[PDB]
Image (cartoon, rainbow over all chains, first blue to last red; front, side, top):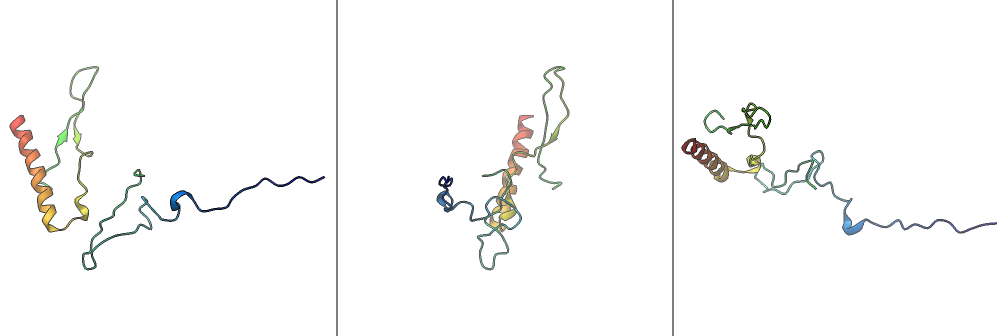
Length: 48
Length: 58
């Protein structure tokens, strides 16, 4: 005897979270001026 | 650093009613590290007011 399997749907996440390293210093991404030597995005661990 | 210090805030003792030993204020600081000259001379102009309000309040 044989039953159909337990279905799933490997899709992308809701609203494309889990694709960008947010809020985690350690491979963190920066908006800045081109000649600025600065950030405008510094992240913290507890912030979501 | 030495000139505009972040003020020592106390802590309340509920049992004895005395002062529980103070601590550096570490929960109101601006994150001015991502700022050029036209604001880090403004942020230091803010802390230099709360270090003068707290002396005209004391």
